[PDB]
Image (cartoon, rainbow, N blue to C red; front, side, top):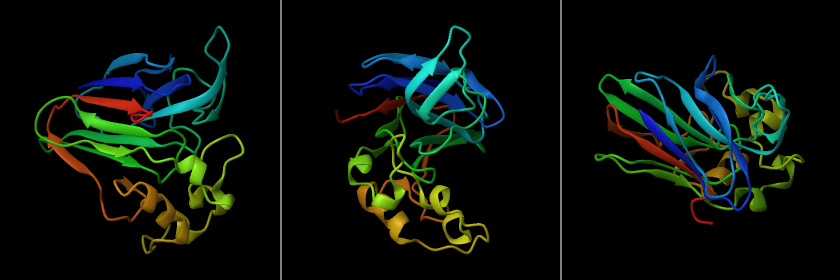
Length: 207
């Protein structure tokens, strides 16, 4: 599956792509404003994620730090990023279909659109100014809007027991971005696409 990752932000982002225990393609790359990075994701990839990282510094060996979405200080991500991170999530070729969604379960850092570039399904978008509107208690000093689980570490926010409901914090993300998961047990906003579709993830799709 091909994913074109486009940075429409006025600022540089460091794109990251991982399945949690491994990089997807090169795993990460710098994307200046307007740059596009095309990656190949292995068919059948289950639980893949693409995100942007902001205010990064990397040395000549690709080791450094990011203010948001840092994946153990690597330019080429092998693991998931440190919240807050808006997430493009996908599972490909799952019983003949692809499943995509955007999630705010790990908070929000950059607005995103995640759409197929092939026929048969619609895209999803979370392009609202979540950082600007972020409740005081969820604001991340390093930038972004944390999810409540990251901030408070409670069974209710983290849905530890599988018996959690929406909260004042999850309702904030849902109000701004109805098309993204706002908590683990949120009514699924997952889109079913034909198996082997191709996609584009666009950071800052509106601005």
